[PDB]
Amino acid sequence: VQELSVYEINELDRHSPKILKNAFSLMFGLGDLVPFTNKLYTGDLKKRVGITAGLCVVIEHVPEKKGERFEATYSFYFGDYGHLSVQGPYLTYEDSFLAITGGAGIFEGAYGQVKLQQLVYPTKLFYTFYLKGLANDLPLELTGTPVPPSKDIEPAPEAKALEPSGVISNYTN
Amino acid sequence: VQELSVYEINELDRHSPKILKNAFSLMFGLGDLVPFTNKLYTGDLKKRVGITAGLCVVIEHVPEKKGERFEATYSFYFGDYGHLSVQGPYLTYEDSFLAITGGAGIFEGAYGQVKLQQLVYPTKLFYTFYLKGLANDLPLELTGTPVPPSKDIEPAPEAKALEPSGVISNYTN
Amino acid sequence: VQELSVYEINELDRHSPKILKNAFSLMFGLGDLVPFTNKLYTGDLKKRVGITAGLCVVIEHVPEKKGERFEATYSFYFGDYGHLSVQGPYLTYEDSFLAITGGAGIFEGAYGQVKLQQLVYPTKLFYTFYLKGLANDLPLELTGTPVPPSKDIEPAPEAKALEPSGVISNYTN
Ligand SMILES: CC/C=C\C[C@H]1C(=O)C=C[C@@H]1CCCCCCCC(=O)O
Ligand SMILES: CC/C=C\C[C@H]1C(=O)C=C[C@@H]1CCCCCCCC(=O)O
Image 1: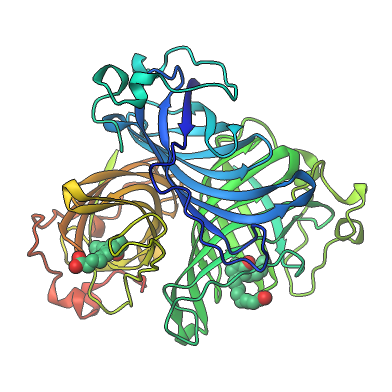
Image 2 (image 1 turned 45 degrees about the vertical axis):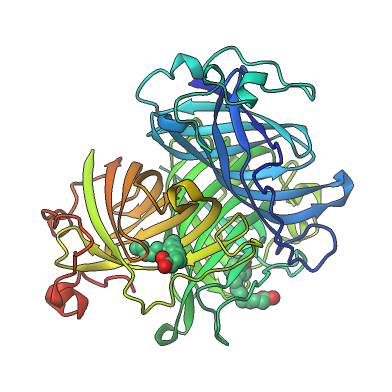
């Protein structure tokens, strides 16, 4: 297993989330679809790597937990390195695990599960991929010691500003 | 290979299915989207395990077969144990095989194919997962001898009523 | 690794693509969903094999490239042989790689990645699957030398007309 952590940040400049509201209910419900795309940073928050991109399908409102259950299908993009794809549950009120459905580029052959931790609803999430199947060790610029997750984390200023020192080559946008 | 069978039943209490109509047709057509979530029971029908959850994308109506072709992306949830994710053909008129795209929890590393068997449209289905890649033998409460599929199968009364003897721990709902 | 090349062609007879417009702009944007299904032919263009089927989720317009980024979830159907499922990036303006999430039939256990090459937007594409995990060698009628990719490719007359010599057994439709 190679652990890979990343931070997903919604900086609200990608038209995301887009809510397609169709459910029988005022609250989120089955029928509601949420296409989305957020920014993706390294686990040590030093570099912008790319984006998340995909679809959240509402399954139910969970009133006891004051939150929603989604079924999510999406990918994580790492510039020229490639991408990872996942499928599984996103619960707005607690951590979950998703399936790693595959990958491309350096992530070809990827399998396993990924831990999803929401830090600030809906703007900050922290992921830990427990990656199996890779052909090589991950590049060092992706495996810096992760910043421990908390509501107070922020990407490095130079990564948010897209300085060359704060981005990977041809980071996904 | 570890065979795992489950029954999927729409008990009409989860607002499912939800039809998002966009095809210019009285019948299902390309454009129509169907988010869904049904109940999942063990193959021996003794216990409630969880739910299915995901999306059926209508591909075409097939008049000569009196049914529809869907393309389906969804997951099968087994309470505290984890989940399985699938992708592939969902035909209302005949049995099919779908791809196992991955899993989480005890299903981490899962791969192979799953047989979707028609039972009673649009209420009951029977599945057999041909599971490869699991870390351990499946728990016994999930691998009781399956009830042979027929139109008149029913979950055990304790399972339907969600009594502790009829559910797995933290059964998904 | 086993390489498998196929041509995907929109012959305008499957109601595809269907544009579900939800972004407020005239251009494609997040919120727009595109269910689709095209015809699939062998790499040597001698035989109809089946169809593609699934969903393109618009992620963003890319004005500097005069094109779109989609996130795609779909399958490739090969008649009685089975199917392959994929997840990943679909860019209207340049080639990409998608993840192979799994398969069924002769493609049970499939993993790897697939190169998507656009030939004519929005009508013709060429794919090269880098397939791992297959139980057997691919059937010879799928592994003929490909026609050189260009905007001018056409299926053999017998394949377009669905004569026995121009189709595989129970080709998907
Ligand atoms: C276990 C099978 C249960 C239901 C089948 C549906 C589903 O979960 C996914 C696709 C199917 C769509 C059937 C639509 C026909 C009926 C629509 C109206 C209704 O049943 O309330
Ligand atoms: C084999 C490729 C055939 C069609 C490509 C489409 C598809 O099957 C899935 C996504 C694509 C969407 C195309 C939207 C085109 C709308 C613009 C029409 C134009 O190019 O003038």
